[PDB]
Length: 222
Length: 226
Ligand SMILES: Nc1ccn([C@@H]2O[C@H](COP(=O)(O)OP(=O)(O)OP(=O)(O)O)[C@@H](O)[C@H]2O)c(=O)n1
Ligand SMILES: Nc1ccn([C@@H]2O[C@H](COP(=O)(O)OP(=O)(O)OP(=O)(O)O)[C@@H](O)[C@H]2O)c(=O)n1
Ligand SMILES: [Mg+2]
Ligand SMILES: [Mg+2]
Image (cartoon, rainbow over all chains, first blue to last red; front, side, top):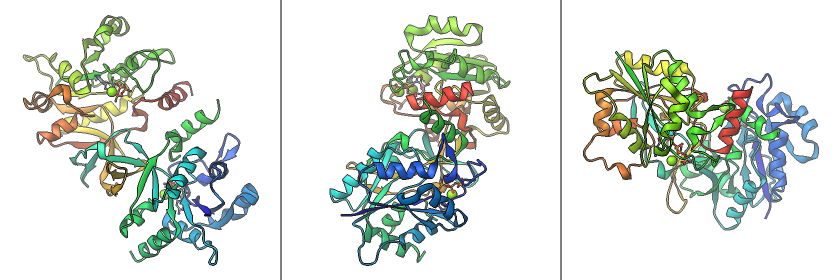
C-alpha cells in the first residue's frame, strides 16, 4: 500500500515576516521546506512527496528539492492549495493512503510520521496527531466577553501530518467544495467520517511567529 | 485605589524536572520567582505583591525577595494556594483590585500587567489577557475518537495576570460549595465565571507563556540571552 504526502507550503507567512515566503526561510542552513520534506522521507513510510509552493517559486523549489519531491503551484488559501495538490494523484494507480503535512511544522520527528501511518494500517480511516492543551482555553464573543471555559479534559491540540484513506480524503474535499477550514480532518468530520487520534510531539509545533522561529533555532543549533 | 498581586509559586515543577521547585529555578542568574515579581512591580501599577511558595521554602523566598514581596506558604494545588494567599488581604483596608499571576510566566512583560489593570480601571469587573489559538482544537473521547472541531474563531488561549474586583474574586474562592482539595481549576476566571461574574478579554503577549517543559525552558533561555 503506497503512501503519498502532500505538503502545503504555498502560504506567505505574514505573521512570520522574515522577508521571504515562510517555507523558503533558511533555518540554520536549511529551508523549512527541505526540513519538512526530510522529516517525511526519513520516516521510512512515505513513498512520494508532493509539495505545493507559491506559483513564482516553483523553479526555486525544484532547485532545492530536486528528485525528492514533486512540485506544483499552490493556491489562494490552504484549501485551494490542497485541492490543487490532490489533482496530481495518479488516475490508474492511486495510493492507499495520503498524508497532509504543513511545511510550517518543519521540526516534526520522523517517528511521528511513522506513528500516523501505523494507525492507518491498523485500519483507522482518518488519523490526526494530538497533544494536551497548554494554556486554558475560553470561548469569547465578538465584543470580547468570555462565554465560558470548556472542560479541558476532553480537548486536544491537533498537529500534522494528518493521514487518510485516499478515497475518504478525496470525497471530503470534493464535497467541501460544495460549500475556509484550516484542518483537513474537519472536512472528513463534515461528511460524517470518523477520525482517530494518536499522540503528537511538541517538536511538531507550527512555526508561525518569530518567537516560534527563535524556539526552532534553539532546538536546531546545540 | 490599591492593586494587590498574588503569585502562586507553590508548584513543584515536575514537568520541568530541573532539580528545584520551579519558582526557584535560576534562569540566567535570576530565579523565576524574582523575575515574575519584577515584571509586576516594573509595571508601575502594582502596589503590593503576595507570593505563595512551598511551605519549606518560605525563608529562602524571603532572602531572595527581601522587601519586594510578602511571602506565605502555599497549598496542595493551584486553587488551594491562591485561596490561602487571599486570606492575607486586609479586611479593614481591602484593595480595590486583585491580580493573580503564575510565577511560571516569568517573562511576562510589564506592559501586559499595565494593560490588564487599565481595563479594570475602565470599569470591567474581571479581565483576562488572551491570544489566538495556535493549533486547531478538537474534542476527543475516551477512546481517542474525535467528537468534533469547535469553531476556532470563538476560542482564545488565556494567560495571566488575571485581574478582578476584590469582592468578586473573594466570593468565587470562598464559595462554600467549593471543595478545595479536589479543585482542578487551571485559572481564576473560571471560578469567577462559575458564580456569574462577567469576564472581559484584553490582548495578551506571547512572552507571557508558561515555562512548563524543558522546551519552554530552552525558549526562555534563548529569550533572556539574545
Ligand atoms: N494559500 C496557502 C496558505 C497556506 N499554505 C500552507 O499551509 C500551512 C499552514 O499555514 P499557516 O502557517 O497557518 O499560515 P501561513 O500562510 O503559512 O502564514 P500566515 O498566515 O502568517 O501568512 C503552511 O505551511 C502554509 O504554507 C498553503 O499551502 N497555501
Ligand atoms: N499547589 C500549587 C500548584 C501550582 N501552583 C502554581 O501555579 C502555577 C502553574 O502551575 P503549573 O505550571 O501548571 O504546574 P507546576 O506545579 O508549576 O509544574 P508541574 O505540574 O509540572 O509539577 C505555577 O506558577 C505554580 O507554581 C501553586 O502555586 N501551588
Ligand atoms: Mg494562513
Ligand atoms: Mg501542577
